[PDB]
Image (tube, coloured by chain):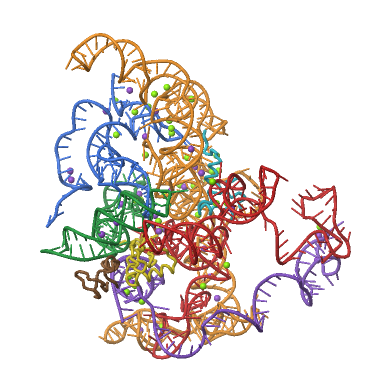
Chain colours: A cyan, B brown, C yellow, D green, E blue, F orange, G purple, H red
Amino acid sequence: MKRTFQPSVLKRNRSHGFRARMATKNGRQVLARRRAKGRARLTVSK
Amino acid sequence: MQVILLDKVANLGSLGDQVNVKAGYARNFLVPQGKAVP
Amino acid sequence: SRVCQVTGKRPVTGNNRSHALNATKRRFLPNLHSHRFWVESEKRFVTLRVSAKGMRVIDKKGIDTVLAELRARGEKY
RNA sequence: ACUGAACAUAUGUUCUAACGUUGGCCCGUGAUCCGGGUUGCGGACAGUGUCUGGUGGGUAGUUUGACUGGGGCGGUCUCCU
RNA sequence: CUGCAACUGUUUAUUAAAAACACAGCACUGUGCAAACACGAAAGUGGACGUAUACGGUGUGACGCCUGCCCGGUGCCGGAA
RNA sequence: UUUGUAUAAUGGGUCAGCGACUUAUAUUCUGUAGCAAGGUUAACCGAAUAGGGGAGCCGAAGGGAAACCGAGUCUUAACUGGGCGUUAAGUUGCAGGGUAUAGACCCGAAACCCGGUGAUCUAGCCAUGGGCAGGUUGAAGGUUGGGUAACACUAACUGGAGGACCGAACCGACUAAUGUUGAAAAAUUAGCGGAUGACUUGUGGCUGGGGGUGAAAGGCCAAUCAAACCGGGAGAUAGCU
RNA sequence: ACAGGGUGACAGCCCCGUACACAAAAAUGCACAUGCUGUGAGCUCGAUGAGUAGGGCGGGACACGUGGUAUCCUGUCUGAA
RNA sequence: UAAGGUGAUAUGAACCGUUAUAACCGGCGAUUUCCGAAUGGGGAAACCCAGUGUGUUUCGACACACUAUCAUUAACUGAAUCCAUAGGUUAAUGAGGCGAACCGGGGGAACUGAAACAUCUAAGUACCCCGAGGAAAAGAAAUCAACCGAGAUUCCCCCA
Ligand SMILES: [K+]
Ligand SMILES: [K+]
Ligand SMILES: [K+]
Ligand SMILES: [K+]
Ligand SMILES: [K+]
Ligand SMILES: [K+]
Ligand SMILES: [K+]
Ligand SMILES: [K+]
Ligand SMILES: [K+]
Ligand SMILES: [K+]
Ligand SMILES: [K+]
Ligand SMILES: [K+]
Ligand SMILES: [K+]
Ligand SMILES: [K+]
Ligand SMILES: [K+]
Ligand SMILES: [K+]
Ligand SMILES: [K+]
Ligand SMILES: [K+]
Ligand SMILES: [K+]
Ligand SMILES: [K+]
Ligand SMILES: [K+]
Ligand SMILES: [K+]
Ligand SMILES: [K+]
Ligand SMILES: [K+]
Ligand SMILES: [K+]
Ligand SMILES: [K+]
Ligand SMILES: [K+]
Ligand SMILES: [K+]
Ligand SMILES: [Mg+2]
Ligand SMILES: [Mg+2]
Ligand SMILES: [Mg+2]
Ligand SMILES: [Mg+2]
Ligand SMILES: [Mg+2]
Ligand SMILES: [Mg+2]
Ligand SMILES: [Mg+2]
Ligand SMILES: [Mg+2]
Ligand SMILES: [Mg+2]
Ligand SMILES: [Mg+2]
Ligand SMILES: [Mg+2]
Ligand SMILES: [Mg+2]
Ligand SMILES: [Mg+2]
Ligand SMILES: [Mg+2]
Ligand SMILES: [Mg+2]
Ligand SMILES: [Mg+2]
Ligand SMILES: [Mg+2]
Ligand SMILES: [Mg+2]
Ligand SMILES: [Mg+2]
Ligand SMILES: [Mg+2]
Ligand SMILES: [Mg+2]
Ligand SMILES: [Mg+2]
Ligand SMILES: [Mg+2]
Ligand SMILES: [Mg+2]
Ligand SMILES: [Mg+2]
Ligand SMILES: [Mg+2]
Ligand SMILES: [Mg+2]
Ligand SMILES: [Mg+2]
Ligand SMILES: [Mg+2]
Ligand SMILES: [Mg+2]
Ligand SMILES: [Mg+2]
Ligand SMILES: [Mg+2]
Ligand SMILES: [Mg+2]
Ligand SMILES: [Mg+2]
Ligand SMILES: [Mg+2]
Ligand SMILES: [Mg+2]
């Protein structure tokens, strides 16, 4: 059966990547929260 | 609005006369035309 | 924005109040109009977005005096 | 309120100068935006603000009793003998 | 032999595929264009680079024969002394 | 937990560890200690757990709505009256019981609101690419002959229409059995429907939560939908267990 | 100097410290002293904040829910001395 | 400051040093790839693609430096349109991003309490947004008081 996760790296980067996050103030707030928490990986960006 | 006429205006008065006109008359016609001043 | 360039009047919030005193939030907007003002000194029309109140101020103080205040505050026209 | 002028007898007609233009042409300009200009057409109307009557399950917050030989329906709910 | 739906389609991913939805066709109604209408405090955008033989809403549901009476109620339309 | 449980009512497989009446401030009462018609200081000052600081607070007088009067006072025109008072114990710590405000003994909703994250599943749409073995049927149109005043009409051939037919791929999902701690959180096997279309599919794009999208089932929006998910208001509230 | 830590057990005198007394080439904070540049104090004579105060309408903030309701703020319409 | 040492894992390898350029510690410097406000353009962060000017060249090529936007100011230029203005170009200066709390301002819930609930409460709280500083804000009476007087603001204890 077709499951929900159907990977596309292009779509992943466009939806959730670093530049997508930086594009909006709410995205920048995501990065600030993740830096504050001290995540090793800020985004899906490879 | 009190204005000083700089020209003969009909049903109003002659040069150098103080007269009370509606603000729109002054603002939009008399003053910009140069027929009166405040 | 709905802001008077002469007076700085802008939307303020308040309540509607029913007979039963139910409060619902509302805004009060300024009575704004775009108006072409004859600037005798500069031999031209200037357009300002002004409240009716601002127009009474301009009548009283004169456009030249008002335009000076705009230039001081750094508001273009 | 922004919103003015004549004229006739609050009402109408006319006017242009506010205001509108999702008409045309010119310029910024390599631009179906925007602004300015010129001109036409509307024109104190339209439209917007504040106030105000109406309408308003379109939307929202809520309410919609208790007793009871289960609950509902019916009856009852205070006072007097 | 017979009910239902004209028909091909669509639907409750994971208990319902149907007589439900849609449908061509029909009718009523709104809409003169900056259209009605819709998204949007707005600017705008869709409707449409369309213009009443068009567009939106509503109901009915191929086709055949047809579609009676009631305007009191509720709505809508019109009148205004 | 109950009127009542060996109950066939509840809970516990067992062990170990953890797991529920607290804290702050105010207030009242009891005990106890100090001082006593008085008791005590707060902030602050002070290196000072000292000392200063008496601003205040409580008490030693009540009555009356109040002015006001005062061991009385109020009521009344006035009391033989009647109500409330009058006979010195209070106050500040410390410990405790209760109350108040706070999550207030602990655990537990369904929900409500705010800000974000999601259309890699799915719904619709947009752009750009791809797919549909094989076999049938034989619309319009045309040609020729017949036929007509000319049409009309008519036979054969040609032609190749269609949400046309049969049927694989592909897309679906009607029946049955199996499976149901599965091979699988929706499948397998045998049959079944559509299969040139209102078809199907790849890649990318757009629509966002009272919002989308919906040939409409309240369907679908990441195995979640009569209001998604994540975080927050937040220890919501729980007259219930 | 009995702060504390370490050392083959729980060390004043084994070690590192501790009390106490000293220390800066360089950069730098702070407090005073003093060059320089800018600065106008003081005195005299004036001036004395208008679409403002106040008001009507609608709201809001003041402990104060518009109430008999002062005062404050102002979206709207006005408007002094 | 020193007889040891080159950070640890970590063992050894090659070494450095012992009276002062071993090492270690402190002051001041130098170097400081790429991404990131990211600023030469673009972009699926850590990559792709340039322009201009200086040089250098073994003619294969190479190095270095500039090149964002916006605001302000100045200069020059410059439409419709005669002046002008809009616009354009260059230069100088500044800004942007990040940050736990505290602070000022713009917006602003609901659960909840009221033993239901609508006024009211929760609460101008949570939250969103803008701005700022080492603190912020407030502040020098068109203030109170009560016929006596006080003398800006802020904070604490009372009043209660
Ligand atoms: K015009
Ligand atoms: K009008
Ligand atoms: K309604
Ligand atoms: K009974
Ligand atoms: K019974
Ligand atoms: K049948
Ligand atoms: K039928
Ligand atoms: K079916
Ligand atoms: K259906
Ligand atoms: K009727
Ligand atoms: K009727
Ligand atoms: K029981
Ligand atoms: K049971
Ligand atoms: K107590
Ligand atoms: K006591
Ligand atoms: K008595
Ligand atoms: K005592
Ligand atoms: K308690
Ligand atoms: K796709
Ligand atoms: K929702
Ligand atoms: K999910
Ligand atoms: K021992
Ligand atoms: K020791
Ligand atoms: K006023
Ligand atoms: K960069
Ligand atoms: K509420
Ligand atoms: K309650
Ligand atoms: K309720
Ligand atoms: Mg409702
Ligand atoms: Mg509620
Ligand atoms: Mg009952
Ligand atoms: Mg039958
Ligand atoms: Mg059917
Ligand atoms: Mg079918
Ligand atoms: Mg199903
Ligand atoms: Mg089925
Ligand atoms: Mg039907
Ligand atoms: Mg029982
Ligand atoms: Mg027994
Ligand atoms: Mg048993
Ligand atoms: Mg049992
Ligand atoms: Mg039970
Ligand atoms: Mg059990
Ligand atoms: Mg007394
Ligand atoms: Mg077919
Ligand atoms: Mg399906
Ligand atoms: Mg099968
Ligand atoms: Mg078939
Ligand atoms: Mg249903
Ligand atoms: Mg799902
Ligand atoms: Mg809901
Ligand atoms: Mg709360
Ligand atoms: Mg809870
Ligand atoms: Mg031992
Ligand atoms: Mg006043
Ligand atoms: Mg006022
Ligand atoms: Mg007043
Ligand atoms: Mg008022
Ligand atoms: Mg860039
Ligand atoms: Mg760059
Ligand atoms: Mg490029
Ligand atoms: Mg309640
Ligand atoms: Mg700073
Ligand atoms: Mg300050």
Residue A46 percent coordinates (x, y)? 60, 45
**Residue C41: in sight, yes or no?**
yes
Relative to the observer, which residue lies in front, D76 or E26? Answer: E26
Judge whether G37 appears above or below H132 on screen.
below
Q: Is residue G14 left or right of residue D44?
A: right
Determine which quarter of the picture holds residue B37.
Answer: bottom left
Judge whether F56 appears above or below H33 on screen.
below
Residue F133 percent coordinates (x, y)? 48, 20
Determine which quarter of the picture holds residue F184.
Answer: top right
Residue F127 percent coordinates (x, y)? 44, 37
Q: How many marks?
A: 0
**The N terminus of chain C is located in which quarter?**
bottom left
**The C terminus of chain C is located in which quarter?**
bottom left
Relative to the observer, which residue lies in front, F2 or F232? Answer: F232
Judge whether F171 appears above or below F71 on screen.
above
Residue D23 percent coordinates (x, y)? 30, 49
Relative to the observer, which residue lies in front, B24 or D11? Answer: B24
**Residue A32: in sight, yes or no?**
no
